[PDB]
Amino acid sequence: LFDENYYAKAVANIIGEVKDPIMYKWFSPDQIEDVDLQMGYQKTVKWDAFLNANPTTIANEVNTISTIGFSSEVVRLNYLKLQYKFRHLKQTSEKFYTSDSYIGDINNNLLPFAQAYKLASSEIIKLINHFVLTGTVSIQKDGKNQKRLLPNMYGLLNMPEQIKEEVASGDKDKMDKIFEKIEAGLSKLELGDEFSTPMMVIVDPATSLKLVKPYACEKWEDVLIQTIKAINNREDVYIETSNLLKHKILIYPLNSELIKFKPSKYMLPTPNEQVDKDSTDVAHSYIDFVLGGLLATRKTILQVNIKQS
Amino acid sequence: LFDENYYAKAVANIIGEVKDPIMYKWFSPDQIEDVDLQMGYQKTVKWDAFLNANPTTIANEVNTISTIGFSSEVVRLNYLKLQYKFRHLKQTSEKFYTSDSYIGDINNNLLPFAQAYKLASSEIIKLINHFVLTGTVSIQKDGKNQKRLLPNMYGLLNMPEQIKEEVASGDKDKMDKIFEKIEAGLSKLELGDEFSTPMMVIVDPATSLKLVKPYACEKWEDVLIQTIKAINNREDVYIETSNLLKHKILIYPLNSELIKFKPSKYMLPTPNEQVDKDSTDVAHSYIDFVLGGLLATRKTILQVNIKQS
Amino acid sequence: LFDENYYAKAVANIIGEVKDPIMYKWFSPDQIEDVDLQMGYQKTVKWDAFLNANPTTIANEVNTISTIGFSSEVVRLNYLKLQYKFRHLKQTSEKFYTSDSYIGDINNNLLPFAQAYKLASSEIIKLINHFVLTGTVSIQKDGKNQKRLLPNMYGLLNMPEQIKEEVASGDKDKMDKIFEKIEAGLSKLELGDEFSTPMMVIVDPATSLKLVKPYAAASSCEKWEDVLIQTIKAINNREDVYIETSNLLKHKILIYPLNSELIKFKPSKYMLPTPNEQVDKDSTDVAHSYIDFVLGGLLATRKTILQVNIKQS
Amino acid sequence: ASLLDSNFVPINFTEFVQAISNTYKQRRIQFYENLKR
Amino acid sequence: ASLLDSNFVPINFTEFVQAISNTYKQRRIQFYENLKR
Amino acid sequence: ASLLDSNFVPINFTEFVQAISNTYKQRRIQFYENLKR
Amino acid sequence: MKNPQHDASLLSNSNEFRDKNVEFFASGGTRTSKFDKLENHPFLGYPYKRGVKRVIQHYEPHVEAGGGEDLYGICIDIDEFSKTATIVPITNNFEGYLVAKDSTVKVKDKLIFNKDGALEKVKATINATALTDAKQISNEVYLVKVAVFGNKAM
């Protein structure tokens, strides 16, 4: 294949230069598990057991014993296939554009296939990270003109049936009020028997700037860490800053029994076999990726929104 | 060569006793990459990609797909070649000055070639460090009588299109006002998607003396470190003091994607082949070095200047 | 490749039946040097030396000597890539058109790929020769609707800063007037220090027919051609003079040396027609193919080409 | 089948895509191995 | 690599184009060798 | 070609200067390897 | 110019991947089909991202910035070295950013090509709909994303 497909050879050679997605920092290694699918839906079944009565004492002869029951629950997950197209120089035309220590038309913004694919893959990975964090697909800083997605396709921020808190616009700069809302949400959290787990907090730059302020010789960040430690059995609490958010705070456990990410094993960018060729030196190529696969239990994510107006 | 040229052999033998430049502590290992040049300009091309629209859902038949564009930017960096000359005793004449515990004329201030070269190289290295930190070439404490340099030859302190804050002479001794200006500049910093990087701060001795003062059981240094951690995703913040600065504060990230240093591989002092000889015992030698090659992105350096009057 | 690309195999098999361009007869073997480029510009640098003062006599001791200076010139040559498309029958569909006497659809004007490519290449080579001679590209006999070309792209006939002579309409039939103009131009020629070089003349058929008349009253054992050859030998240091006829010219006379130091042709190595890898296929029996060719690359020193135009109006 | 293996030689585009997926999975595993908090 | 040499076996279209250019150059050289004005 | 490598025997001043540059680069790399902030 | 050849001393801050596509150098269209017909023609002037009209005068006919009843297509790319413009015929659908006359064009507004080849709010001989607001990119240059689909009867 490599003897025939120069583009496949180039992809195999330059696949290592693409940086790792930053969304991996938001999950534990056990929380992520790939699935084999491109587009469609997939049903997940979770089994449980419960005790029906007090246990039976085994003495002398007895036939009536307490029972253990079972239960099941089914959750549907949707997966969507998306594609992009990019232009590049034809393989046989690179010799006519190899300049001094650089290849490609500076005037016409034409690149070799390997560099074009690397840059496009990086951009697509950034878009995938944005979708996973926010649950929406948009290329604008406002967050508008969002692409319409299927139901059962949510991010960490828009997952339904979770603890939503809202800070009024009048208290947009009152860290005491923000922390009061955070404490209320933390109290409303329901971890059950899986409370002994590390916790992850994701904030925006303005929230981090407010956090590093003194607590009204302790900081709001230290107070928040202590409060979360009071509920997570004195375990690790990680704090992260993301520019993708705007006046939002996300708190969730890094436990595979509560939140599980099951992406398609084709989620990350993959070249398409089709290449558009003509009589000129310009060709076109396609990159595929797959979105969807976040699964969570009810009342395990705290989402705080600080209204600005 | 060593059989014929004694000066080359002496340089090879004594080159290992010259101390490393102190400017290496202002950069990360990946932020420096040598280039092959002595004098002239070099053009660097940076390629970028962007998404033109939302991705396209691949369902049923479709031929109109979203596109990914590409961009190029050309940056010109200038390099300047500079030289120094120094006097030394001739090798064949050293035997007549090889006294006890030293070699040379204390009366006439004459040294052997090896020692003269080592001392001259150390002085030139200090001058290169001064240029790299400040962007100007001068040998005076006042800073006047600066050598005129070419455009596109900038240091960390005079790099254009960066955040520049000024503290009024009325508040020249008010750490609260200085820190307010620092916060303003930190907010105006634009690290974009590369904010998760260690940060470096360079201050003058007077600024360090003011910083170690109590905050108005916390120190201004700790407050500044926390404030910078608020923006660099809570990563490492390094603080350095340089006697080459006067009432200045420099803050910048140690990220190779924002600030890069491409010095000539002949930047550090190198002997010249030409040696001046006559009938006397005094000879002259020349040392060459190259200046230039600092590349930065816009609005990624904070420069605070405290007016004295 | 030949086991998978029938079009490439056929082009390889039939490339030998295309005749050589006629532009080769207008240049010496050393005057033509290929360059490796398809589209863009290429720069040439020429160095010269000069004396600043009289030489210095070396006697006894002296430190101050006379100097020799240097200078340079830069010349930029542009190149352009052009393409043509043509329709033909598919390889697998030929057996349904292979008649007893020929192959192809006469009623629909469809040929096999080999013959179609040969004819298209011949036409393209004719166009290339016309461009090399005249500096213009057009498909009309009137010469209108010309393709707009790049600067620094000239032919032998439109090269700027050369010697131009015009024979008036009233004297269009007077060989004496024509040779008066030719002598004036030959005097105005400036070959510098390379004057001892062979010379080449290109004439249109009408002028060539005028050149075989007896020299003029009428003479014997002497022709206008011999008079012209003697006149050119008067300036080329009695070197060889060649005469060529080209139907592409019309009432034009072209005189230029065959010295590579003065006039040089640096064509691209892909100037002559070359097939394109792309072949348009469909569900029918008709396919399409593309041919590429590169134009440009003539360099000449100024005031070294004589161009005489005989006006008809 | 991983692109990180030098000896690996794919036969067709399907195997190439499988190798790409395996390479991405291995890179994720390596990232979690090298990650420090 | 030229089309005149029957031993030449092209591998790809780039080699084919190079052979075509070499054949054109060799034909020009032969024409100038055999030319006699 | 580095002055640190004692086996290096220069042939001319050009090679000597190249060795000096390589030695400076190696010293910078060693300094960054030994650096501990 | 499509890509002004100016050498700078700094790298432009372009790390954020959002709001990075509304640029003059972004040639072509936001959404492109394999079966879009593209024609290269000689041009006079600067018809980049503008409607073009054929001009016949001796040289072959060229194209230049224009609009109205004389519209022939839209210029989406320019090669300066060969002085050739890529044009999408008016009989072909197009979607991309084009030059706007002023910052008065809002979303959903119907647009017409003027004498200079710039898009302005409505008389319309073509079907053009603005998809985004007018965005300033230069001293007085405004770009608007517009979908152009064929002619408009009467």
Image (spheres, coloured by chain):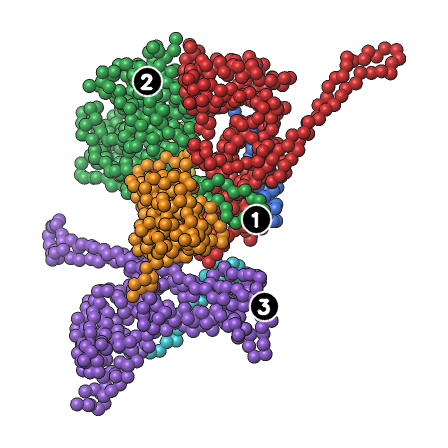
Chain colours: A red, B green, C purple, D blue, E cyan, F yellow, G orange
The numbered disc on residue C93 is 3
As measured in the structure, the alpha-carbon distance from the residue carrying label 3 to the one carrying label 1 is 31 Å
Residue A69: horizontal and vertical position, in percent?
A: 76, 21
At 46% from the left and 16% from the top, the residue drawn is A178
The answer to whether mark 2 and mark 3 are in CB contact below 8 A is: no
Residue B119 appears anywhere in the view: no
Is G23 rendered above or below residue A258? below
Q: Is residue A66 left or right of residue F10?
A: right
Residue C67 appears anywhere in the view: yes
Residue C261: horizontal and vertical position, in percent?
A: 27, 65
Q: Amino acid at mark 3?
A: Ser
Residue lying at the far front of the rendered structure: G154
Q: Nearer the viewer, residue A208 or A168?
A: A168
Front tag of 2 and 3? 3
Q: Secondary structure at mark 2?
A: helix
Label 2 in the same subunit as label 3: no
Q: Amino acid at mark 2?
A: Phe
Label 3 in the same subunit as label 1: no
Sooner in the amino-acid sequence: mark 2 or mark 1: 1
Q: Secondary structure at mark 1?
A: loop
Residue tagged 1 = B61
Q: Nearer the viewer, residue C114 or A154?
A: A154
Q: Quadrant of the C terminus of chain C?
A: bottom left
Residue tagged 2 = B179
Q: Amino acid at mark 1?
A: Glu
Neighbour tally class for label 1: few under 14, some 14-19, many 20 plus, Cα within 10 Å = few
Q: Chain of mark 2?
A: B
Is A9 rendered above or below residue E31? above
Front tag of 3 and 1? 1
Q: Quadrant of the N terminus of chain C?
A: bottom right
